[PDB]
Image (cartoon, rainbow over all chains, first blue to last red; front, side, top):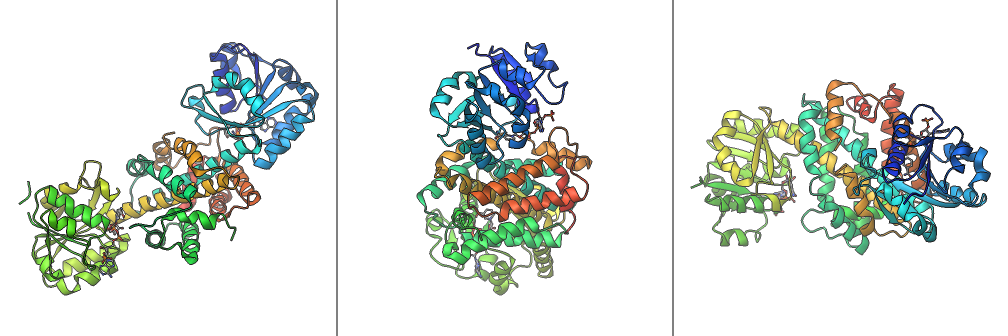
Length: 287
Length: 287
Ligand SMILES: NC(=O)c1ccc[n+]([C@@H]2O[C@H](COP(=O)([O-])OP(=O)(O)OC[C@H]3O[C@@H](n4cnc5c(N)ncnc54)[C@H](OP(=O)(O)O)[C@@H]3O)[C@@H](O)[C@H]2O)c1
Ligand SMILES: NC(=O)c1ccc[n+]([C@@H]2O[C@H](COP(=O)([O-])OP(=O)(O)OC[C@H]3O[C@@H](n4cnc5c(N)ncnc54)[C@H](OP(=O)(O)O)[C@@H]3O)[C@@H](O)[C@H]2O)c1
């Protein structure tokens, strides 16, 4: 496949995507608002477009990887009319609603539109280990799936453009919450002189089974959260201990308190005898 | 390799696993539980069910206690407070570092040696090399009994402070329940569009496996948080999208609101251009 491709936005993700398109043999044209981020890509045969319009004109497939909808629109407005008949693959949707605005805006200028999302480190881009997911017209995805495969694995999610954006914010939700839990744990143990370097191996070990993911999934889908011998009321006591320990060590407690509140809400609704997974019930209900 | 008599007090899932491990390693094992009926499989494998706590403590130089918390541990051991002198008490059920210290001081006052233990694995892992149990307390005591504790799995000494094992335990529990909650928020995010959890899990599992925990520990230990190409200010704006997407999907927003509030504190402290790891600077500071 030698379909020409354009990549707009050369943050670390845009650069890895352009690099992957080149490595797969596509003629790649790149553009960034800030000059000087394209040197390695040019050295590997990318063409550095001088204007957005020239960038859009170079390819039937335009991949946009910039901060958000507002940046995407300001970038592309001067060349909006040049989008007619091309496919815009957008990895810059900050919300499911903005993705649908973006799809509509693209439609009013003659362009098909896929929303895209990937939650992997840039270096994994262009390897089978990168899982990229898309939503939007299935016929548009099927038509370009072979070019997009240069980026890694591809998953079609369905026709609603906001789907990919929804998955991305969810994964973003899991990531930053996880990262915050880690830093809270490091501060907890740090309050006794335990260096984060010494604690990190225990922390990573916590994540080596990843069994909880399928088991919680199966519980959520079946709508049944069998408590067994590690119930939610038990788990709430554990989170109490986190709070107590945090207070007594000087560490801030806002984060474990928020977790506590969620568990309490689930116990106040009769799941105190169910597994932790049953907390999804109160999460579906703004409080 | 054993026949050393071991007593296990508390026959919840962990205690039964531990008693089974001691039996498998060849140790004459006495068990006692508040609730009768949970010892049948252990007695078939050779364990002795003790009539009373006092009898169970007396049976063995080494007394392992895995119950809910210190308060329960103290309730059961009250009638056996005389029998304790001359033994070592291995507490695998301290809820907080402070309760572990209280336990140690209480054991000392009754003529008993004291080791605090933190178990970081599910009960099925106990007794296998996948189990890693950390201990704190007097090194001599830990050394003299390591060969018996080896029946449970790996053993790691953390230091002389008896609260250390509990600290590691609660920090790991803090990372665990915070991650679970993030995962459920995510799942509730996609679920609000009819997406099955079953499906979403593949992408969540990829978050892990792809890591940087050791990278953030280096930064924590240096006290230097280089922003590079993803600063705290950009991460916070991202978290804002999570909140906004959550409100639009009608999901509860308490958990991401809590992550965002932590980010905003570190930005108010002047870390907006540093990496997210700099948020630890406001965790060490009760707010
Ligand atoms: N898949 C998704 O749905 C999705 C959505 C958002 C973010 N992300 C991920 O988040 C990470 C980084 O997020 P990010 O892309 O916001 O950060 P980033 O790495 O800083 O990339 C932002 C890009 O947007 C450009 N940009 C921003 N505002 C602009 C404007 N007003 N006019 C022109 N260009 C503008 C920047 O150009 P300059 O070089 O000129 O600054 C840069 O190329 C990446 O891993 C990315 O994949 C994924
Ligand atoms: N996988 C795990 O669950 C896990 C992992 C690591 C560490 N731990 C720790 O190991 C310990 C035991 O946990 P577990 O998994 O076995 O489940 P658990 O539900 O914490 O076990 C509670 C045990 O304490 C006893 N108990 C509670 N209150 C009592 C009281 N007032 N008087 C007398 N006995 C009382 C219970 O006896 P009854 O049977 O009569 O109720 C039971 O044997 C806890 O400290 C827990 O944090 C557990």
